[PDB]
Amino acid sequence: AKLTIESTPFNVAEGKEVLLLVHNLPQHLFGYSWYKGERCDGNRQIIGYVIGTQQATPGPAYSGREIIYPNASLLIQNIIQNDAGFYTLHVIKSDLVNEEATGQFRVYPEL
Amino acid sequence: AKLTIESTPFNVAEGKEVLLLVHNLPQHLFGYSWYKGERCDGNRQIIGYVIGTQQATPGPAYSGREIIYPNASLLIQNIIQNDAGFYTLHVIKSDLVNEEATGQFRVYPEL
Image 1 (cartoon, each protein chain N blue to C red):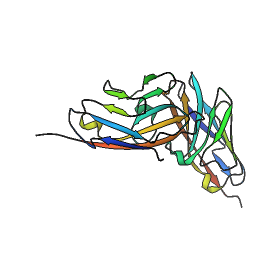
Image 2 (image 1 turned 90 degrees about the horizontal axis):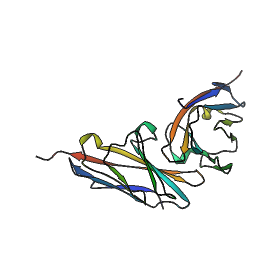
Image 3 (image 1 turned 120 degrees about the horizontal axis):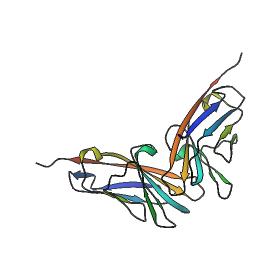
Image 4 (image 1 turned 30 degrees about the vertical axis):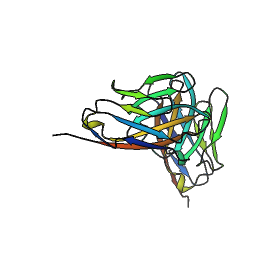
């Protein structure tokens, strides 16, 4: 029912990768908008994807490391400390009363 | 150039109405999402509108008083104190790297 992001691992070692799994996508979709952070700050949008045409456009915050998947999940590679924090997904429904959810993960150094 | 909301009046007397004018809409649009507040909290979405089909759907926060206009402006009638605050617009571009902007207004009692 409720849209949820679960990061996996919740704790990502430096240089490895996180996957943000998306659960309970609503019906009547259109595409997805993924932001680093907690609000919809377009200046820190990673990516947007149109379900209908499988078209994936980078945003100001995209950095060469992020991958998006048809069912909204988003993986981020070769992680660094500054990646730790919140990530908010915005699922744009076709009638534009959209839904949003945010997840986080943490990063840590090995020794 | 930069997307901006200007409220008018910035100071709305109780029972009167505010109009949130939208300036410098970007190109390649699709529709608009209007939220009470500063972030994209779907639980306080007022309304969404699809430019292509002139279709306007209410959100959880819609309250019977809000009107949306083809070029994104949004008026709110018979204003009360609790309306004062921020309002964020989210312009959903067709490739889903969207833009956002927020405006405010203030409300005040006459005597």
